Image: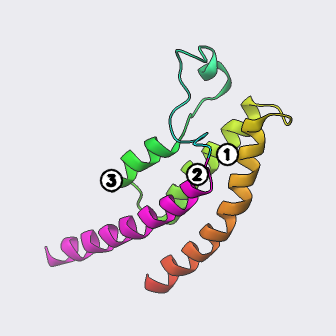
Amino acid sequence: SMEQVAMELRLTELTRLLRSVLDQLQDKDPARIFAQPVSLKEVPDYLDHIKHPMDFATMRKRLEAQGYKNLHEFEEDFDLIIDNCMKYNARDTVFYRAAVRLRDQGGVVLRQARREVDSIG
């Protein structure tokens, strides 16, 4: 149908905007701490601690399959990255501290994203 196409164009355009959002958030992680999945070879107990692992590469795979229906879904995955880190790692660690800085800096990007998503519809 023509309606299904229009819906698909909307999804494609959301994917475009979320790709730019993802790039801007990942720039706030210049150490690449959150770039890839925590390695279960190197942290064998990880899934005993963290039930839903997340990282920027995993988000990018979902994004490119147009697997984010709305900004809320995308933010859920970004918050997982941060929240998983802040539980597994202690306050006095470079990992925890990286997550705090990512959260604080990402907030600004996500605030305007929400306005753009609502504005453009």
Q: Which SS class for mark 3? A: helix
Residue under the image location 69 percent in, 37 percent down? 85
The three-letter amino acid code for the residue at tag 3 is: Glu
In magenta stretch: residue 48: no
Q: Residue furthest front?
A: 31
| Residue bearing mark 3 | 64
Question: Magenta stretch: dominant SS?
Answer: helix
Which dot marks residue 31? none
Q: Residue furthest bottom?
A: 119
First in residue order: circle 2 vs circle 3: 3
In magenta stretch: residue 23: yes
Q: Residues within 10 Å of mark 1 (few under 14, many from 20)?
A: many
First in residue order: circle 3 vs circle 1: 3
**Relative vertical location of residue 47 with respect to residue 63 in this rendering, above or below:** above
Q: CA distance from mark 3 to mark 1?
A: 22 Å
In front: 113, or 27?
27
Residue 3, position as x, y percentages in the image: 21, 77
Residue 92, position as x, y percentages in the image: 86, 34
Q: Residues within 10 Å of mark 3 (few under 14, many from 20)?
A: some
| Residue bearing mark 1 | 82
Which dot marks residue 78? 2
Residue under the image location 61 percent in, 68 percent down? 110
**Boundaries of the magenta span:** 1-30
Q: CA distance from mark 2 to mark 3?
A: 16 Å
Q: Are marks 2 and 1 in contact (CB under 8 Å)?
A: yes
Q: Quadrant of residue 45?
A: top right
**Relative vertical location of residue 16 with respect to residue 117 in this rendering, above or below:** above
